[PDB]
Amino acid sequence: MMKIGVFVPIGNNGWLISTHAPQYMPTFELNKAIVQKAEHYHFDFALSMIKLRGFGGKTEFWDHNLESFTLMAGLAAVTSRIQIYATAATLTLPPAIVARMAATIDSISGGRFGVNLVTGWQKPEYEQMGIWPGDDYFSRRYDYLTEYVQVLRDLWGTGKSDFKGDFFTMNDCRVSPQPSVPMKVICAGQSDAGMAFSARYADFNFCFGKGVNTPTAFAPTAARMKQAAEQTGRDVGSYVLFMVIADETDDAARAKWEHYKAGADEEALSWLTDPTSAVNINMGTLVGSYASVARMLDEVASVPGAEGVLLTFDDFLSGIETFGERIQPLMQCRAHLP
Ligand SMILES: Cc1cc2nc3c(=O)[nH]c(=O)nc-3n(C[C@H](O)[C@H](O)[C@H](O)COP(=O)(O)O)c2cc1C
Ligand SMILES: O=c1cc[nH]c(=O)[nH]1
């Protein structure tokens, strides 16, 4: 059995960098339609990233991005069952503010909220607003994140912090109310330091799916994460990111994938800098008939450590509908749904 989440398009054109891919702005109403349809099909969770600078080109790729906490606060108000995760770019928000924002969305959602904590990697997202700490941050960023999460855990657990470190000084810091349920923390650590952080402080770790139609190719990453979790004695599973391009036949899905690769927005791809393609940032891609994708997702569910998948689509509104109507009913790992 495996959990399914939707990675909501908080940035324009989702995860395809192509003039032949669907062209759309991230609105609230689009993300509302996506999350309500996901909830209707018993998706377990919805997550938004945070992306503070785009890649330009013909498609202005990720030049247009909403902010994650405010988006997910709006989505929490128009849902009732799906788990809601927002991403904190921890260089941009003081931990006491994230603590209070999480208590707030806990109140909006009736205990369905969690936080994805990221260090940030892309210097320009931070340099552009004068808040990059310097190139020491590449090596020290999980030290920073360790202090950050200690402040969050004090505030959510007791309502107060006296934490004092290299990066934070709390003098009887107060945040109440405390969340109604234990606050879920997720991390997207791929490095040794990142997985060591996740093993100590996260409920689950997000990793990248790998290759095109090689669903189990990420297995060594999920194995590293299981070894990290052994070092803390904590149950910290892997949720794996894939793009699904499904149709009625294998040949039809392959034709769509090829059509997207042929439109690659090369100018946007240079800023960024059966194989994976830069057209979806070399994402793990599952391309097939509804039945072929259901079989491949059942193979993901068999990989040691894999507890769920985070899904993008080529078209979210039609991709969620065909997932719910044609793919999910054939998945052995979703036989637990009503
Ligand atoms: C599903 C997923 C979501 C991510 N979201 C973001 C994000 O919103 N913002 C960001 O700066 N980095 C994000 N990242 C980058 C991770 O935090 C990334 O794997 C990490 O920065 C690289 O691993 P390392 O930090 O251990 O080297 C994401 C990664 C994954 C797998
Ligand atoms: O940095 C990011 C954010 C979302 N999706 C990715 O593949 N990378």
Image (cartoon, helix red, strand yellow):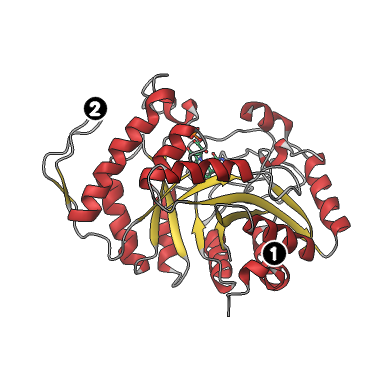
Q: Quadrant of ligand 2?
A: top right
- According to the picture, the residue beneath numbered tag 2 turns out to be 166
Q: Is mark 1 within 8 Å of ligand 2?
A: no
Quarter the C terminus occupies: bottom right
Q: Quadrant of residue 177?
A: bottom left
Label 2 neighbour load within 10 Å: few <14, some 14-19, many 20+: few
Label 1 neighbour load within 10 Å: few <14, some 14-19, many 20+: few
Q: Quadrant of residue 290?
A: bottom right
Proximity of marks 2 and 1: CB atoms separated by less than 8 Å:
no
Element type at marker 1? Answer: helix
The answer to whether residue 248 is left or right of residue 283 is: right
The image shows residue 173 at horizontal and vertical percentages of: 15, 45
| Number of the label disc, if any, that sits on residue 263 | none
The residue that appears at 54% across and 64% down in the rendered structure is 35
Q: In terms of depth relative to the viewer, which is nearer, 27 or 274?
A: 274
Residue at the far left: name it: 172
The answer to whether residue 161 is left or right of residue 123 is: left
Quarter the N terminus occupies: bottom right
Q: Is mark 2 within 8 Å of ligand 1?
A: no
Name the residue type under label 1: Ser
The image shows residue 183 at horizontal and vertical percentages of: 33, 57
Residue at the far bottom: name it: 338
Question: Is any part of residue 84 visible from this angle?
Answer: yes
Name the residue type under label 2: Asp
- According to the picture, the residue beneath numbered tag 1 turns out to be 318
The residue that appears at 62% across and 30% down in the rendered structure is 272
The residue that appears at 60% across and 33% down in the rendered structure is 55
